[PDB]
Image (spheres, coloured by chain):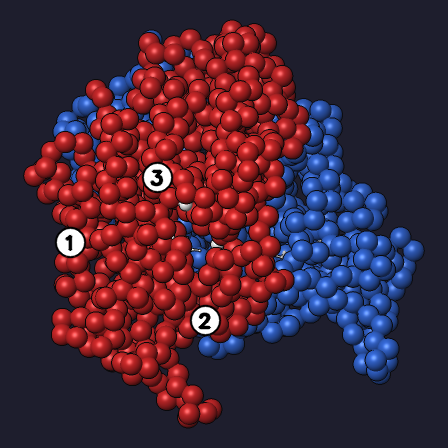
Chain colours: A red, B blue
Amino acid sequence: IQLDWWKNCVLYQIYPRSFKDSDGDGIGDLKGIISELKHFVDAGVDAIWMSPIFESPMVDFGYDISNFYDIHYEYGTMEDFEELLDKAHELGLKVLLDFVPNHASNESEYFIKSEAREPGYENFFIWADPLPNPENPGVRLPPSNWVSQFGGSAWEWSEKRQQYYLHQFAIQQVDFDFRNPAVKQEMFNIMKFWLDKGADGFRLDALPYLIEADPADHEGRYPDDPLSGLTQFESHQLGYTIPLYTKDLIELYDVVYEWREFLDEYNKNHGGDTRVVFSQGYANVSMTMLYYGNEDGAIGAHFPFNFDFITDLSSKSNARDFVYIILRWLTYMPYGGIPNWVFGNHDNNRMPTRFRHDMVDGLNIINMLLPGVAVTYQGEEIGMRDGYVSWEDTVDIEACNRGDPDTYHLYSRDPARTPYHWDNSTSAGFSTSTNTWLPVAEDYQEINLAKQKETARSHFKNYQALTKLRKQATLSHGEYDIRALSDRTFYLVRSLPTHDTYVLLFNVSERRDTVDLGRVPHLTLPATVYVSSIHSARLAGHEITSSQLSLEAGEALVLKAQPI
Amino acid sequence: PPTEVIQLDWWKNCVLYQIYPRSFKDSDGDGIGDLKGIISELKHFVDAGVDAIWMSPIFESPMVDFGYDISNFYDIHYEYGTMEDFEELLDKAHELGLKVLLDFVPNHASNESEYFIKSEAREPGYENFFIWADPLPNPENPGVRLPPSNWVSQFGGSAWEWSEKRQQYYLHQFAIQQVDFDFRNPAVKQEMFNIMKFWLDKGADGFRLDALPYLIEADPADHEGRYPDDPLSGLTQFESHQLGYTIPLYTKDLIELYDVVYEWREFLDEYNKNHGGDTRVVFSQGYANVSMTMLYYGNEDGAIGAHFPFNFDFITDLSSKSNARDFVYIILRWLTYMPYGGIPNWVFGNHDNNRMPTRFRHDMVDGLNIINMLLPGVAVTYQGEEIGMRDGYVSWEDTVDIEACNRGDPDTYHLYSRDPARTPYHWDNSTSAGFSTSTNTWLPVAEDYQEINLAKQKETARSHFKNYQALTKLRKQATLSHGEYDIRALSDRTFYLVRSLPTHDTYVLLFNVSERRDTVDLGRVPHLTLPATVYVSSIHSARLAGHEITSSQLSLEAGEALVLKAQPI
Ligand SMILES: OC[C@H]1O[C@@](CO)(O[C@H]2O[C@H](CO)[C@@H](O)[C@H](O)[C@H]2O)[C@@H](O)[C@@H]1O
Ligand SMILES: OC[C@H]1O[C@@](CO)(O[C@H]2O[C@H](CO)[C@@H](O)[C@H](O)[C@H]2O)[C@@H](O)[C@@H]1O
Ligand SMILES: [Ca+2]
Ligand SMILES: [Ca+2]
Ligand SMILES: [Mg+2]
Ligand SMILES: [Mg+2]
Ligand SMILES: [Mg+2]
Ligand SMILES: [Mg+2]
């Protein structure tokens, strides 16, 4: 039976500001994306989601939204967006928008009206009174010790309103009150507006932070978060507190289930292709699985993002660690759940930087060959590395607020946001201008899409071979078997009776490894190399005939073998 | 017809039972368990379907750490009995077909050992038997003596004790009275061979080897001729005398310890080659991360170590906070990380940790013993798990565990004390649960002995003990010794474990580990064809052994566990 599109799509995250500049201002834009929609068809991408493109002061490059109903002028107009949707659908692509429900810009009308106590907006954000200060009574203390994800107090004093407002993110990102039925209605209004425009669904931002302790349950006070007791964190630094009262509250999931109830209604009433929500939240695996639904029968996000290849694996990982981490989502996911696999995003170091340059193909093979949904971040299809960004060039508010000239590199997301490497032209073909909002990585001459399209073997040609492979019943409907053959090498087998068997072998280590292919289930020899790492001695079409296989450091093969 | 199978070597699928001799059976009314006690109940292990027993330490000991402080590694502690009682235990155990393993503590000796008395005196052959160090130079005021480093004892305080006699510090990672051997001393390493040969020659079938993570510490040659400080944890809740104040980078899990273990295995392999009869084995004790734990089996350069390291995952990583997905995921860790050729093992308790039904729940006893017995490899049972013994209440006044006496006080002792898991075994409802004829026992008998005792569980229709016997009996079936395993969660509440083998019966555990009821589709369980028969059920299950499962829809109560017997694949 053929699956609904979202159950095995290749999903590509576009960071619009760094994708394509169509107008020589050094800033990626919608006309730029429209100009390269054909790239997604060439790559074998099914669906694109864009990081935020709504009206925003750009304090957090779009995650601070001042109007949820119109396009950010630097990216273009409502008309450009409508054209992007039209041409993407024409090419067969699905298009998801980055919805940011936790917070609004302090330049939003919601906030201005709330700060001024305009009726029906007074309780739109979290507003609280100061505490008195025993050590210097002149210096007001905030309602609680809560710490912002971007450093300092999560509480900002409003001169105008004579109260503190909550900001789990930047001072300029103001936390909506999700116990307010008017806030919750406004979220339906925003989603209805963009679905009415033709959007294929939403990526839902920062959900762990939706709800904080109600002061009603704590004698009218905001309860302090427990202390970590780690001496490397001072009271203004993220890590000083354990976010017991400020993150992963059980009530956040009820909001998500209400969103899915609304979306299921909409899909029923409008028909056509299913519109989906994919949720973003870094949390422990059990809190992450409540985004899918709960055991009482609630249904949530079509899936929450799996960040395990970001959070729990790196160049420090061995083959047993790879297998053990891959098994986590597969062990914890509810029955009928769609697995997904994320290798990078705009908040984390790029895939080849976190792992090694020689592991790029193996990592893209894992993404494409595991059951479910492959997620690609902008650049991973060509093996883009972290770009060098000086203190002087750093614009990430997280790095500016938490960091300084000596430390900024511990915090900055900018190195994973440097402009896309189209070719070896000025600014790697991202712009006609040499003034890119972030500096272009120094290695764009070695690493760009044009070069990879015209070399016999490249990351991009491997990417294309893998997205093409996902059309095979073996990958859409086959079983999986995964195990380590040593500390250095593991296998992943997809099998399905009467259909071809596909086997990943991946030496994730820095050393040669010789493995016994007789230990691999469902693998009969001779077998044919379908894809090999760009540094493999073995080419596509090569026959593997010996049961003893030496893999070089980082080497990955996909073998096509006889059906079970 | 059912295929023939070649029987496994004994140690690859034994049920291994840990005896804590002080708490097992008092034969003489002193309230202290003893060897004649154990001899009198060797038939209990045959009745239970145990293949091998290991005893916590019975060697001469001042009893500061109840046997782990050994003053003579070549004789028996007088409270437990004599060498002759030991020889008698071995003979009668072997006559009944049991294997017997001794617990040997290689890391440290009693300060009452001749080794330490000779070492403290700088006697030739023994001066460098232990780790002796000068004070750290304190030029900033030479008046005050500083210890060699900030190292913290596992039992609280400095790991360094000043000897007025020798005018140097000695290392004790445990109690002041437990002195760390120098494992870079070839004479120490040879003495460890001499001890194991002596007990193998008596006819021990092998050893459990204690506290192996602590064998080797940093060599001052690598740190400019001083003992390097352990890094600070920087946790606000620990001061410099408190375990937790340091990270044991220079004091635990050093790579050189594994070379000692591989040398033990080399010595044992040669001994087995030169004596024949059944393989003698070493099982290693070490609490460490999974990568450091698997190095006990061997390494990927071909080194071979312990027959296995103990798997403590059901103690360290699962509890009553765990759901069915946690259970599966933790079970998969040993199976994923274990090297090719390695024998899995499963440990639910010991003399250092809370009892299984206390860590989990009282309603989970059967399900936990089923997991132990149905998983592939070796089931390890701690004294009392076969009847579902719970922790005993032990007051501060009755607390004798040196770790609690050193680290704890009237308000805190319960955080550290191992005594609740060491309370005397519940034989029956007589005086002191039939452990002793006296009302005076070395630790108090748990208050629930009238409700939880072996004799009662033999007389009643359904019991933890009767389920245990049924499971150890099932382990003789080819499906459990030789069969494949499949394990997955059906929900957050219920997982399955299927043992299957073409032409032999299929066996399926279904376990609701949650506090809520769960209904599951048995159609999702691989190799399960209905109708199927309940082989074992939890003592409060709606289903008795022999109950026919015909419906593909199965409702399980909180804690309920079933083993189903189903037609061969
Ligand atoms: O380091 C970023 C920080 O924020 C998270 C929260 O889920 O990411 C999302 O939310 C932020 C505020 O809207 C954005 O800055 C970020 O870009 C967005 O993806 C996590 O990545 C992390 O905790
Ligand atoms: O809490 C006790 C402490 O010691 C360990 C070390 O592996 O256990 C063994 O070593 C001790 C000293 O010989 C004994 O007191 C203990 O009974 C013995 O099992 C661990 O359980 C722990 O780290
Ligand atoms: Ca919030
Ligand atoms: Ca030692
Ligand atoms: Mg532009
Ligand atoms: Mg970060
Ligand atoms: Mg006695
Ligand atoms: Mg303890």
Q: Nearer the viewer, mark 1 or mark 3?
A: 3
- Residue A10 found in image quarter: top left
Mark 1 beta carbon near ligand 3 (under 8 Å): no
Circle 1 marks a residue in which chain?
A: A
As drawn, the label of residue A152 is: 2
Of the numbered discs 3 and 2, the one sitting upstream in the chain is 3
To the question of a shared chain for discs 1 and 2, the answer is yes
Q: Is A436 placed above or below B544 here?
A: below
Q: Nearer the viewer, residue B63 or A87?
A: A87
Of the numbered discs 1 and 2, the one sitting upstream in the chain is 2
Q: Secondary structure at mark 1?
A: helix
Q: Residue at x 44, y 63 (%)?
A: A150
**Contact? badges 3 and 2 (CB < 8 Å):** no
Q: Which residue is labeled 1 in the image?
A: A189
Q: Secondary structure at mark 3?
A: helix
Label 3 Cα crowd, 10 Å radius (few <14 / some 14-19 / many 20+): some
Q: Secondary structure at mark 2?
A: loop
> Hey, what amino acid is under mark 3?
Lys
The residue at the far right in this view is: B124
The residue at the far left in this view is: A269
Q: Position of residue B201 (x, y in %)?
A: 71, 36
Q: Which residue is labeled 3 in the image?
A: A31
Q: Position of residue B421 (x, y in %)?
A: 46, 58
Circle 3 marks a residue in which chain?
A: A
- In the image: residue A360, left or right of residue A11: right
Circle 2 marks a residue in which chain?
A: A
Q: Is B281 placed above or below B408 here?
A: above
Q: Residue at x 19, y 53 (%)?
A: A190
Give the spatial CA distance, label 1 vs label 3.
27 Å
- In the image: residue B8, left or right of residue A298: right
